Image (tube, coloured by chain):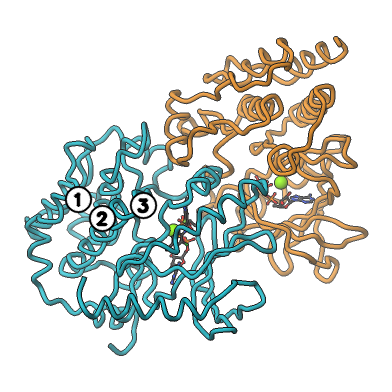
Chain colours: A orange, B cyan
Amino acid sequence: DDWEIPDGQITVGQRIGSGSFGTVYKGKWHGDVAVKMLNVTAPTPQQLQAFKNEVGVLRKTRHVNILLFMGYSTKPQLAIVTQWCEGSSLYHHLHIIETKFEMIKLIDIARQTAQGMDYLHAKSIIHRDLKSNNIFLHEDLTVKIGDFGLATVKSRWSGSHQFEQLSGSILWMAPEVIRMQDKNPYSFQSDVYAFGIVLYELMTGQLPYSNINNRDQIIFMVGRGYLSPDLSKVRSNCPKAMKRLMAECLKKKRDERPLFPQILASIELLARSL
Amino acid sequence: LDEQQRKRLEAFLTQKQKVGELKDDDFEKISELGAGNGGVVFKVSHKPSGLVMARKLIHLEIKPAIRNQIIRELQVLHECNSPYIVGFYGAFYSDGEISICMEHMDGGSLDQVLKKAGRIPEQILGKVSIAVIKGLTYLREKHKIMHRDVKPSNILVNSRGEIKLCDFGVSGQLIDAMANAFVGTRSYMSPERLQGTHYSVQSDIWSMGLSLVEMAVGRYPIPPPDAKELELMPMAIFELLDYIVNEPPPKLPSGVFSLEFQDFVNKCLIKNPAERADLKQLMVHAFIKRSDAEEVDFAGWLCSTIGLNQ
Ligand SMILES: Nc1ncnc2c1ncn2[C@@H]1O[C@H](COP(=O)(O)OP(=O)(O)NP(=O)(O)O)[C@@H](O)[C@H]1O
Ligand SMILES: Nc1ncnc2c1ncn2[C@@H]1O[C@H](COP(=O)(O)OP(=O)(O)NP(=O)(O)O)[C@@H](O)[C@H]1O
Ligand SMILES: Cn1cnc2c(F)c(Nc3ccc(Br)cc3Cl)c(C(=O)NOCCO)cc21
Ligand SMILES: [Mg+2]
Ligand SMILES: [Mg+2]
């Protein structure tokens, strides 16, 4: 119950890219891992102990559809060490490589994703940052959900106050999360909303708000309830029971959205049904 | 036009001819200039021609079809040749990053210059508003492309006293790919754009106004300064956009700036785009008519402020 990796253990290699709260390097550590050099460079010792606690809970997470959290380091700089996926992010498949999956396999991707999410909520873990960039397709088949939790390194602390600076990608963000108006905007249904957007990806082959090209325009209108993903764009042959499920996750008021126990259930029903 | 500009404009075209195909091995990194939430910029030396340029690197994760369109659209920038637009050498793609190669402006963006200076003098903001009004004109008339992103960090200035615009929406597909950026700190987006659509040049004029205020006082002006913070002469991104839409626009202090200036920015910050001033009107406003007559020494004020020798 004190998980830290020392220096000289982690062979930091190629610079892979940067996200909403760190920069990732492919490192080595008893095999390929993923080394994410957090953006909170100088951690306050009140922030530093909250991070330690949260790593404890991410460490005890073990699920087929979850990327293993292997602990962290602090030697050069504060960082994070997780499994290395040889797959490509679902985002890459859908919007860059434009992989041509069958509807049978699309629905399976949705099923395993709700499968993993359901375990996280079962262990009372809010992802906070569920998007198709954080979903890899390991060996081109299994789904693996990374970048979960970690509320304390995505908050930029003052001295002892975690005031969540809205960051992440604005798509996938539930309206109440956009607004940052009521304390704990991140909730199990904020994740369901995110999940619903990822269904939109799967069912349409497009990101939401394709006809809008203004970052701040989307932030304001979605937060105000004026903007909503155009479900018209769902492909011709996507199940009727599927589109309805997507629409329930996208409800503007969080309390109307379903939780994952029910959501996963819904997916398995239309799964065998064809 | 005049004679010192027709020289500098034609002298660029000559060095630009010395540059042929832009390849990533023809470049030698010198220093980092700045970074943003979607790009980083380096001062670099083009070995085949020794030119020193600036080289912005945008790492986008887009499909190649979209990417190759972006590169194509970015070649219209070989037609933008104005003393009020940053020089453009070429754009290309390599190693997963779009490079845009522009001329070095050794003073930096006014957003850097604001930090080194704290506040900027109205006499200087006078000459600045001139350049930005000329730059936006040349873009609406000669190219029918609108900047769509006027902010202090897109106004570039150099030691020869030039003020130039850059980072303007010429690539309509880059605009689409920019839209999946994460949240920023703040926003210079006019209130109609946050609701509707780019309302011709008028929606750029708002941005220029907001930017004049921020540079005039030394603080992003949303929300407006406190009662005693002002006599001393943090908000969520969503709430700023809600304030820009559902609250009266910012204004200049009180007695600290002229009335010509206070009025100039007040006409720029009208929340209705149609009632807002247009380029034709700002061009002959009192504050602009005066600040054009003033013989301000900009190049000197800049090098002073940066900390160099005139
Ligand atoms: N565990 C991992 N294994 C392999 N590649 C990874 C891993 N985690 C992230 N990456 C890649 O690293 C790059 C950037 O990572 P990252 O910082 O997570 O950005 P992001 O996931 O797109 N946004 P966010 O996760 O919300 O901060 C992308 O090309 C990812 O596909
Ligand atoms: N030609 C140039 N000469 C000198 N400095 C430059 C030049 N182009 C860009 N810069 C600097 O690079 C910095 C950041 O680049 P940029 O990607 O435009 O970010 P930004 O405009 O400041 N903010 P953002 O639009 O949110 O990314 C600017 O603040 C300038 O100081
Ligand atoms: C959205 N969008 C559409 N077209 C664009 C465009 F041409 C851009 N670049 C550019 C244009 C003219 C000159 Br001169 C110099 C440059 Cl570097 C940028 C841009 O670089 N924004 O900067 C954000 C941070 O990277 C954006 C564009
Ligand atoms: Mg990721
Ligand atoms: Mg810019």
Quarter where residue B38 is shown? bottom right
Q: Earlier in the sequence, mark 2 or mark 1?
A: 2
Secondary element at tag 2: helix
| Residue at (55, 22) in percent of width and height | A230
| Residue at (88, 61) in percent of width and height | A29
With respect to residue B7, does A21 lie above or below?
above
Disc 2 residue type (three-letter) = Thr
* Residue wearing tag 2: B137
Of tags 3 and 2, the one toward the viewer is: 2
Asked if marks 3 and 1 touch (Cβ < 8 Å), the reply is: no
* Residue wearing tag 1: B279
Question: Residue B238 appears at what percent x and percent y?
Answer: 42, 38
Q: Nearer the viewer, residue A132 or B154?
A: B154
Q: Nearer the viewer, residue B267 or A225?
A: B267
Asked if marks 2 and 1 touch (Cβ < 8 Å), the reply is: yes
- What is the C-alpha distance between the residues marked 3 and 2? 10 Å
Q: Is residue B153 visible?
A: no
* Residue wearing tag 3: B147
Disc 3 residue type (three-letter) = His
- What is the C-alpha distance between the residues marked 2 and 1? 7 Å
Question: Residue B218 appears at what percent x and percent y?
Answer: 28, 62
Q: Is residue B72 visible?
A: yes
Asked if marks 3 and 2 touch (Cβ < 8 Å), the reply is: no
Q: Earlier in the sequence, mark 3 or mark 1?
A: 3
Question: Residue B253 appears at what percent x and percent y?
Answer: 15, 54
Within-10-Å neighbours for mark 1: few <14, some 14–19, many 20+: some
- What is the C-alpha distance between the residues marked 3 and 1? 13 Å
Quarter where residue A99 is shown? top right
Question: Residue A268 appears at what percent x and percent y?
Answer: 83, 15
Seen as rendered, the residue at the extreme bottom is: B309
Chain to which the residue tagged by mark 2 belongs: B
Disc 1 residue type (three-letter) = Leu
